[PDB]
Image: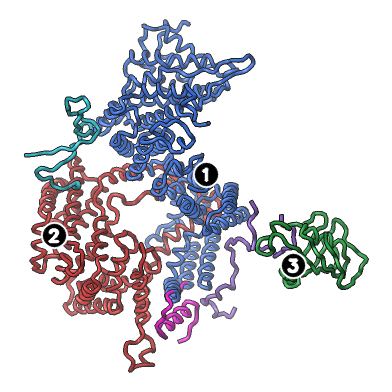
Amino acid sequence: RKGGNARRHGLPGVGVTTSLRPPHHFSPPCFVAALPEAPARLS
Amino acid sequence: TPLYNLPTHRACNMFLESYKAAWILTEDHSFEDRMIDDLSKAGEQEEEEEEVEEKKPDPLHQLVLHFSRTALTEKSKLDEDYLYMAYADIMAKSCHLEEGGEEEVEVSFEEKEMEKQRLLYQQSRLHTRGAAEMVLQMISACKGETGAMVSSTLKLGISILNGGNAEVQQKMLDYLKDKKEVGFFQSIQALMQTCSVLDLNAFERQNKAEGLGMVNEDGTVINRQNGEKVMADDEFTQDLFRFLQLLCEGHNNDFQNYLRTQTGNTTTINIIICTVDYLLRLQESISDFYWYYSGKDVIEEQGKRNFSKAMSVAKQVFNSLTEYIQGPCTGNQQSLAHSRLWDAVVGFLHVFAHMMMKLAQDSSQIELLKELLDLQKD
Amino acid sequence: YFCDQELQHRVESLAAFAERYVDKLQANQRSRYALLMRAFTMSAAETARRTREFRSPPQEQINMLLHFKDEADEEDCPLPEDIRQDLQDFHQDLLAHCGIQKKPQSLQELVSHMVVRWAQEDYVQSPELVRAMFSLLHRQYDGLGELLRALPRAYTISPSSVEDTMSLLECLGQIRSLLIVQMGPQEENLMIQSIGNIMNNKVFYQHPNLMRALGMHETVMEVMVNVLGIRFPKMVTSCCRFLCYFCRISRQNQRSMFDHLSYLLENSGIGLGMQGSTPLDVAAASVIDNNELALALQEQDLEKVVSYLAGCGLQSCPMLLAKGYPDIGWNPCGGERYLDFLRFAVFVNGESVEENANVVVRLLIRKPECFGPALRGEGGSGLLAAIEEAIRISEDPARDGPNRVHLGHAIMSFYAALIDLLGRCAPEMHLIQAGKGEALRIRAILRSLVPLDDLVGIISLPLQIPTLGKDGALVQPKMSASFVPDHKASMVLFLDRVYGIENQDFLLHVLDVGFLPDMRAAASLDTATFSTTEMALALNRYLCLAVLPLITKCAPLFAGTEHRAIMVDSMLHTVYRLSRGRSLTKAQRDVIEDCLMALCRYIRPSMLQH
Amino acid sequence: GVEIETISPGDGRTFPKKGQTCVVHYTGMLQNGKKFDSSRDRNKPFKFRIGKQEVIKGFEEGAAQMSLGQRAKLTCTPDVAYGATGHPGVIPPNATLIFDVELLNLE
Amino acid sequence: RSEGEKVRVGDDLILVSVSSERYLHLSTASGELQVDASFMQTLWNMNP
């Protein structure tokens, strides 16, 4: 947008990323729950 | 079949693959000379301490020392890593600038000598920084495991030793004689025993496979065929015997005697006799190939290519055998006289005596005949 | 991380230009296609179009269109100047972004100068740091090569499949997660579930190239390295379930799995994958129906499998004697597994590969103990004696039993597999006519190995036809324990492959002994009560596969058959009975009908009156 | 069965009914005085349905018996669940519990 | 001894047929000590 600002790299990590990444999964720590092979425990 | 009815994403995949194979791959770029020069500059360390000797190594020196450290570590096998592969490739292409130069008219003696000077400088840039020892260490570490690691190490060693310069030969000989190790020569013997020859069975299999010509998932043409099964690692075995030649180039009698017998070590491996044995195997394979084409009137294109590969490798083996004895080293002359060299020579004489007539009875094989006569000259 | 994001940005931008450019390319191809269909009178231009933008694989089409970077190539290309210049501009800015072309200005110069300064400042002594700075330095200096190495992993997918590939990546996520963890019970169950979901995903079938790019075949193979390097039979059962289906997905996947064929045969054992799926099975699935891989199959793998076959022939199965079955001194089941693999290697597309057949017969004949107690001089017994003792074993439950494994059935299935392998190693008819020396000698070796009288005897012993027994019920024989017509089919394969049928007297003798009884059994079981009987189905497919297809090519020999004319009459009567379609597949029935017509055009009308 | 003892009075008038997800923050201990499960420390309150018993049964009973705005210590007898073969790594298999739970903004 | 090596006087070796691809074997089970081309490999000495 500065006219002569072309031919300069955009800063790494400020652009839009579209590569498919499996989203993060976390289970909140609960222990008072009645604990009842077993499914994979989340972090 | 039209590209328009193909799905958009799959069309993008074909575009990416063919663009990669057709533009970026062919888009060459030279950075090895610049980056080796930048690593060889020592910076400001001498400015801060002129009076201090045994200064810290240059960045390139530290890099070579790191590879030497990983080479000298104790391990069952040398795991492949692209870091050293890329760096050895870079360090070889730095010295190869004067090898290629960057129809052959005469060159001024001044220009030729100055090209030798440029090559000597570019080789000094690496062999004053431990590269001469590091190639030996990694060849000894691979323990005769054929792979891209030993391939890159051999190519680098050829790059340092091009022109048969005596400094690197002296450093290599001093290192071997002092460390007294046998791993290096055992590894060389193992690699030479695992070098391949003309098969004549993989030839029939590959000929029938190429004549098959079915349509796979890759398209009408099978691009996933094994490219060369008849003579694989031809470029490896040419580089191996080129390395053994460049060890003794310039008539370095000390290294020639070292190759024959390594006194000082507990075990001696006669590399000269082992080279003769590989030559004998190659001679038998070429004779078998000639018998395969003995009845045929005209050798087809695949047969001509395979003879070219085998004969070029035989030319390199012959040159290295010559370089083992060009300096009048009576030890190697007697060793070859008593070895099985005579049988190999007799076989090659028979192959040429019939192959010359077989090619001379046709005009389209004139290039193969020229290469054949060149091998006979060697 | 920041360098990695720079590279990711570059490859994403390349994909964005790919999707921008394919639309223009398709539009230009549409315009040239419309012009070609508008005017194709000029034969030279019509053929040029019919080679460039017609009748070519899309990969070749796009390669030829995109081959214009050199000026001489660009002199004659179907692309327009606007699209051409757009691509040249994109290549130029790609070089600018890779830096192809004091104070740092860009990330590349920043990291390069920083790393060199760090090395010049002091002698670093932490090896991990050393390789870190030089790895970053190499990546910064050689930018284009990093993109070259990254593009194999780059893949582009349609938006409509995004969710399915997210599930794909999640499943692969836990496969890699418990890759590094030692195998346990719940860990095994979790990865069984992930393999089940990896089945369920549709992108598994509709994108095999991205399957290779993700390379989960490598991951699951290394999981095999854990379990095989005996433990977790469920894991060994789930190995082929994904690996072999991956082979079936596409030919290139089969190539990729063929690259690992040495290891599978390296640990190939009958104790490995004892039930259902097997490393043996993935080894064979890598060679099924591929002449190129059959030819590329190197002979030391065949050395491995012949050695293992000899090992089975040496001693009875340890698992079998652990079950408590009587000691045989030689394993039928493992031998038959190995013979199935060898058949898949030698034979392909209804053809015999000459070189594979040659090395296979040479190795098998080199180790005489492979064939078993029969077909060896020390044993002093033949194929006939083998089938008699096998039928006695199946007869008595004292030696048949020690529950689902039956020793007699295993023994004659092993010998059936051996004979079928030899028949599939038999040389081709045209080769034997042309007089290839090796083909003639291989057929001679097979002739010496397997005597003809044994074959006709084994055909002459019939099946055990299912009986009514109690009224209102149909008691059937146990095919899994007794002699089945599949053994007959593999047996007569040797007849139609090695010896052939060139004598009319021999032909009628063969039909008299063990062939006409089989077709009478078919006519007897043609009733609807026995139509769906499994033994009847086995005999039915035996007929349609081996019996009458031999008869069609033996039809010219049937001309001039006056002696034993009523035998031919009864044969054609039964051929008509199975020509009437009662519980018959369309292809099976058509085979029977074509055999009937081929007979009718050679048998005498003065004979055909019944 | 639990021994519920009020600590600070609250509304005392709205008690949770069967079929409502209630939100509670608590600091659970063992009989020794052992802070191991503290949603106050985690800064995240916990939600539980009464009737499904997604929460431990003794806590569920005591939470039904208290009111909004009020805190009570629930002395949980080991007959509440995972009273044998308890949650690994946090609670030994057979032990007691106490929970100084207050209810806030009953749903 | 390796394939492609010269054979010296009094060297033991295995004669494998080209016609039948079968070893030269000493069959002594009959008791007459006959010679036949069978697959039990049998060493042989070739003395000039």
Give how far across and how far down residue E7 sits, in percent: 13, 45
Kindly report which numbered mark, 3 or 1, lies closer to the viewer in this rendering: 3
Say left or right for C385 vs C2. left
Q: Name the outermost residue toward the left.
A: E48
Q: In the image, is C548 to the left or to the right of B115? A: right
**Which residue ends up furthest to the right in the rendered image?**
D13
**Amino acid residing under circle 1:** Thr
Q: Which chain is blue?
A: C
Q: Which residue is mark 1?
A: C237
Q: Which residues are magenta?
A: C98-127
Out of D81 and C264, give the one closest to the viewer: D81
Report the mark closest to the observer, 2 or 3: 3
Q: Which residue is mark 3?
A: D30
Answer left or right for B358 relative to B51.
left
Check the image and report above or below for C57 versus B89: above
User: Which shade is chain A?
Assistant: purple
Image coords of residue D92 (percent x, y)? 68, 62
Q: Which chain did the renderer colour cyan?
A: E
Task: Specify the label residue B378 is tagged with.
Answer: 2
Element at label 2: loop
Category of crowding for the residue at label 2, using alpha-carbon neighbours closer than 10 angstroms: few (below 14), some (14–19), many (at least 20): few
Which lettered chain is shown in red? B
Label 3 marks a residue whose chain is D
Q: Residue at x 32, y 16 (%)?
A: C503
Q: Looking at the picture, does residue B171 appear above or below residue C285?
A: below
- At mark 1, the secondary structure is helix
The amino acid on which the numbered mark 3 sits, given as a three-letter code, is: Leu
Residue at coordinates 35% horizontally, 90% vertically from top-left?
Answer: B46
Which chain is indicated by disc 2?
B
- Please tell me the colour of chain D: green
Tell me which chain the residue with mark 1 is part of. Answer: C
Q: Is residue C38 visible from the viewing direction of this image? A: no
